[PDB]
Length: 316
Ligand SMILES: CC(C)C[C@H](NP(=O)(O)CNC(=O)OCc1ccccc1)C(=O)NCC(=O)O
Ligand SMILES: [Ca+2]
Ligand SMILES: [Ca+2]
Ligand SMILES: [Ca+2]
Ligand SMILES: [Ca+2]
Ligand SMILES: [Zn+2]
Image (cartoon, rainbow, N blue to C red; front, side, top):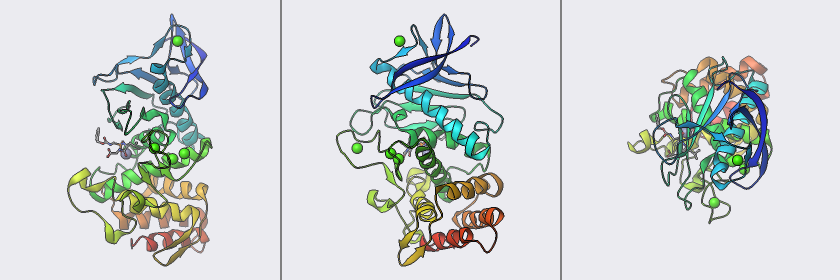
């Protein structure tokens, strides 16, 4: 909407206070004009029609329980925009500052979040498996990264390409979580998963097997559930990414870590210059090796480490 840029204040899902960019025209709307062509947050009102209504508030204060998922979706979309712009020189998900749209309060007891082809969508959870999912910065960045993937490599959402698609979202979700630097880790969704259980998460990149996911190509799932295991087999690539960054010895294969920034540069280049809609794991290995070669040179430690990591997870 047309209006003047303002700064509201509120509390997120975890009870933390933050400032948010809003727009004033009669009401204060969750419309952040400071980033690209805007970040817009909508109320789905417990229903499934999308996007719902642009979030309107009378006083620019967002401290109601109902406000919390909107505050975090809006704010963490901003952080994710900043990561892509500042770290990768990418302007929004399409590279041309497309408006970023999110809807919260989707459906009832909805234990998931997704990119629907046009926007991000967040359930509130059922209060047992999840609390409102926008409370996780890794979750928000995971969802926006699906949009980046769709506009770039275009990895088809099934089987190996789909598992790469998922891993790309977990990798950048995690790198955004480190960028914001609040309780960062290599776990996925820990901030909004199972409020009654401490110390767990939906997935782990450092040890995917902790939550039943494969950490070696020999353990890949090839059934039909979960689109051919896109959230399962992602563990193989998540493990490789973790090893590239942090190092370690996995099934006897030692990897020299090169750090998060270089992991991010290598995978961003692979995503945007080499991967295609049908890439499999072997082709991802080749893309990451080529990307590291471009950035650091054929004889570099970075290239050697990428090879070590894929060797470690059984991907040739
Ligand atoms: C980071 C998580 C908290 C949320 C994350 N959600 P996600 O991977 O975006 C869900 N994916 C999804 O719904 O894809 C199906 C789809 C939806 C809409 C259009 C096209 C395809 C997840 O791992 N979900 C688990 C699952 O769906 O099994
Ligand atoms: Ca208010
Ligand atoms: Ca964390
Ligand atoms: Ca995390
Ligand atoms: Ca938990
Ligand atoms: Zn996903």
